[PDB]
Each structure stands twice: as C-alpha cells, then as structure tokens.
Image (cartoon, helix red, strand yellow):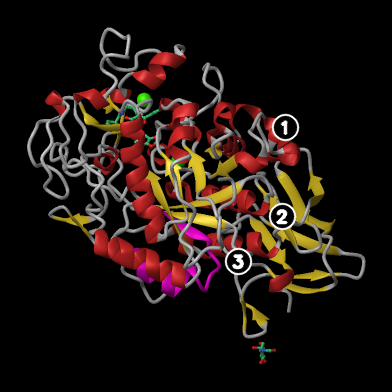
Amino acid sequence: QYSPNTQQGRTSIVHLFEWRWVDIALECERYLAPKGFGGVQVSPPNENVAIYNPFRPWWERYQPVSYKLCTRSGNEDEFRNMVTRCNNVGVRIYVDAVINHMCGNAVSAGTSSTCGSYFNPGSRDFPAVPYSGWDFNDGKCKTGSGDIENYNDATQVRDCRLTGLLDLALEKDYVRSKIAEYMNHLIDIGVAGFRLDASKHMWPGDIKAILDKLHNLNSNWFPAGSKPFIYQEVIDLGGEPIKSSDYFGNGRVTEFKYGAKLGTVIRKWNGEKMSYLKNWGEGWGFVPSDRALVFVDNHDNQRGHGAGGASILTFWDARLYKMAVGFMLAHPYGFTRVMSSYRWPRQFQNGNDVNDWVGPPNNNGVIKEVTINPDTTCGNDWVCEHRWRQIRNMVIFRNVVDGQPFTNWYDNGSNQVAFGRGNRGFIVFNNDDWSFSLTLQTGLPAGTYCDVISGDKINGNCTGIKIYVSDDGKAHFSISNSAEDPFIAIHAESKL
Ligand SMILES: O=C(NCCCOc1c(-c2ccc(O)c(O)c2)oc2cc(O)cc(O)c2c1=O)[C@@H]1CCCN1C(=O)/C=C/c1ccc(O)c(O)c1
Ligand SMILES: *[C@@H]1O[C@H](CO)[C@@H](O)[C@H](O)[C@H]1NC(C)=O
Ligand SMILES: [Ca+2]
Ligand SMILES: [Cl-]
C-alpha cells in the first residue's frame, strides 16, 4: 500500500481537481505522458448530492448518494475510457474514495443527485447502495448533537457525524463489504490506488479491514500481486489526540504540516526563514518520508481556512507558490502531489472568502471543457499549474534526480539557500530582499546547463539562463530579488 505503482522514473501525481473524465484522458495522452507525470488524483467518481443552494459547490462531491460511477465528471463508460487510455500511456489514476460518510443528515430527500438515484437522509435510506438505518453510527455516537463537537475526544471524532454528514458503521462487515465492492470495481477497471477521504474520522482497524478485502491491481497493466497505493487524508497538525502514525499500518498519510510550515517559511512569518530548511523532513516533526504524501496546497486548504489556514500558498500567490513547489519537488522527502486548480471569484470579507464554495467552471452547472492555448496554458478558467513551465520542469527535475541524496547544502543565514541531489541536480533560491550572487559547489559534472525555471533546453540550446559548471563542480549563480522567479534549477538532462 506504500508504493505508488507509477512507472519507474515517474515521481509525482497531479490532482486534476473537478476535471471531467474525457479531459483527463486527453491530458494523459497529450501532456502527462510526454512530460513525465506519474498519475492523476481524480475527484470522487461516485454519485453525489446535487446541491443547488449554493449553486453546485465543489464540496457537494464529498456527499455520497451511491457508488454508481456517475458524476459531473462523467459516467462509467467515460471513467473506464479514461482509466484505460491513461494506463495505456503509463499514467496512473488514483481515486478520491469518500467512504467515511454519506450525505448531510438534513439534506432533503428525493432525486437531487448526479445520477438521479433516490435517497432519504432523514430515514437513512440510500437504496442505490443499498444502505439503511442499520448501516449508520446513530446509536454508537455519544454526543448530544450527533455531530463531532470536540476533537479532544478521539472516539467521537470517529463515531459521530463530521459536519452533520451521515457516518457509516464501518465496523460492520456488510458496510465494509459494500465499500470494498465499490473499491474493487475501481481496481478491476484499472485504478492504481486511492486517497481515503476523512481518514481521521475512521478507526485505523476499520480501514484495515476494508483494505483486507481489496484486490491486487489489474493484471493486464500491473505485475502480479501489486497492491493499491493508499494515502489516507489525516489532518494532524499536532495538539489533538489523534496522530497520523496510528494509520501507518494501512498506507501513507497526507502530511499537512508540510505545506503549513513551508508556507510559513516562504512567507517569512514569525521570523522563519529558508535557512532553517536545512533539516527539512522528520526534523520538523513530520511523519517518516516513506509514509508521507506531500503537497504545498490541496483542494480544501487553498481556500484559506483549511489545515494551515492563511499560511498556505496557492496559485493566487504565483511567485512564492512556484518557489514552494520547486523546493518540494527538489527535496527528497515524501511522495509529491502537485495541485491543479480552477479560478473562482475569490471575495474576502472580514478576512474570509465568501465565494470559497464556488464549484468548477460551468455553463448552467455543466462543467466546462479544459481548452489548451497555443502557449500551452489552459482556458475556460482552469489554472493548470501543472503546465506552468516552472512547475512542469520541476516535476521532471524530480524524475531526473530520483534516488540521489540531499547534499551540498548552502545558506546565507537568512533566505538564500541551495542544495543538490547527488550528482544529478542542483537548485538555488533567493527569498531575501537583496541579490544572491555567489559561486557554489553544485556536485555536478562540468558543462553548460540550462536553468529549467527561466527556460528550457530546446534544440541543443537554452532559452533562459545558462549556468557554467567548472571542473571542480563550482558554478556562479546570480539571482536578483526582482527576478520573475527568484530560483534557478539545473539537472543532468538540462546539460548541453
Ligand atoms: O465549512 C464547511 N465545513 C466545515 C469545516 C470543514 O470540515 C470538514 C472536514 C474537516 C476539516 C478539518 C478537519 O480537521 C477534519 O478532520 C475534517 O472534512 C470534510 C470531509 C468531507 O468529505 C466532507 C466535508 O464536508 C468535510 C468538512 O466539512 C463547508 C460547508 C460544507 C462543506 N464545507 C467544507 O469546508 C468542506 C471541506 C472539505 C471537504 C473535503 C475534504 O477532504 C476536506 O478535507 C475538507
Ligand atoms: C543554438 O543557437 C545558436 C544561436 O541561435 C544556433 O546557431 C545553433 O544552430 C543552435 N543549435 C545548436 C545545436 O547549437
Ligand atoms: Ca466515522
Ligand atoms: Cl488531501
């Protein structure tokens, strides 16, 4: 459950948040395969509540109605077509598995659902599964409201309703079996693994019992006996009783401290600075690297009041964001996930975005296609961070340097830092309010290297900055604090 099942030499996944299946299939073929991406985290592919007040928010997809593969992203045939096409070009699919809960207990009964299935939250009836009142934790939860009230009580966090979402009785073999039926349908289609949503809200042992029912990966594409990659969404910033280490026997965990702390450092909050990153990793209180799924932002916390609150860097903070993503992709800790977002009309009132619910770009509720512009950016309000040169080239950097040790660290005691990855890559950052002009030991073979942040190696030439490494491994780097991107990265495959 710990290995991503990507092709050798592909080291990241991208969250194509709210993308349609047909667009992901095309993206696999036209971009993700040639540019070395390992796989795609998809939005929940199972039927959810259609919420019209407010209008089709992103978060309706975290309110299941059934396990039919029928959503605003597409139907089952479209989902299978995507998985097949992506696997056929060596790009994996990871499903966001929403298995802790069904929909909100106060959602009105009827057929306001993405496949038109009937459901009745008040009577606990989800006949398209089927689930009934016997399948929820009403009787087990001990809080006066029936909802989670206090995160200092680890039992209610697991047995009570997260935000009122009907909480499945995951101790029951019937319920475990219905979830495994859904997950095995997906595995047999060809999915490579799962994000387990809301894992903090499930007992480690109930997750384990579900995972024990799962198949090995589809043997038309994967070696015999391959286990699905599992990454559990556990929001653990410290200071609560539940620790993500309780989940290590099941799979990896999301390390939300990673982006929270990286954001504070890059924003220079509370006296933090990039020189402190020399011991980034477990020295910062993080989980073991081999259990970490890392990211700068995710779909929830990029809206500003998730895990990390306002420290989280996002595409809205493009300059600092590229820096943070670059540091993450260069540094060996963790398995990396890159975010890919849509734009929405963010509107802060009293410090909070009142439009943080807005769903993906749409016409009358129908999600818009991703259009590709001649310059390789996206239209229709898709941000496509994973296509930004500075991010895509760092996805490739991570592939090139895979397995190489962290070495040749430099810092100026403030916010000018650099490090290498064995003899295969080197990266230099300037987040101070003055210039960084210095000769540094790079660990690389002598030669001329293209900076992959300011440009590309194309047709035996560099389109941006060139770095000259001498026989001693040293090279001069010059980065103004006014540079478009105040960091430079070079690697073995950017050498002329
Ligand atoms: O203000 C909201 N919710 C309360 C604060 C966020 O708490 C939630 C957490 C959450 C927050 C902090 C924690 O420490 C924690 O253990 C859990 O996880 C969820 C997971 C879901 O599948 C569905 C949800 O509705 C939630 C949720 O509401 C709005 C309105 C409804 C959805 N929502 C949201 O804000 C939706 C957020 C959301 C949705 C999916 C996620 O995976 C997620 O992490 C957050
Ligand atoms: C590199 O750029 C130079 C100058 O534009 C050009 O003469 C040369 O043909 C290009 N390609 C190589 C492989 O040198
Ligand atoms: Ca639960
Ligand atoms: Cl996540």
Which amino acid type is marked by label 1? Gly
Q: Residue furthest right?
A: 472
The relative height of residue 87 versus residue 5 in the rendered view (above or below) is below
- Whether the magenta-drawn stretch holds residue 31 is answered as yes
Q: Nearer the viewer, residue 206 or 458?
A: 206
C-alpha gap between disc 2 and disc 1: 22 Å
Residue 27, visible in the rendered structure: no
Residue at the image point whose x is 20% and y is 24% from the top = 133
Q: Nearer the viewer, residue 91 or 255?
A: 91
Residue of label 1: 283
C-alpha gap between disc 3 and disc 2: 13 Å
Residue at the image point whose x is 29% and y is 17% from the top = 147
How many numbered discs? 3
The mark found on residue 454 in the picture is: 3
Instruction: State left or right for residue 211 relative to residue 126.
Output: right
- Magenta stretch bounds: 23-42
Q: Quadrant of the C terminus?
A: bottom right
Q: Position of residue 168 (x, y in %)?
A: 30, 28
Q: Secondary structure at mark 3?
A: loop
C-alpha gap between disc 3 and disc 1: 32 Å
Q: Position of residue 404 (x, y in %)?
A: 76, 57
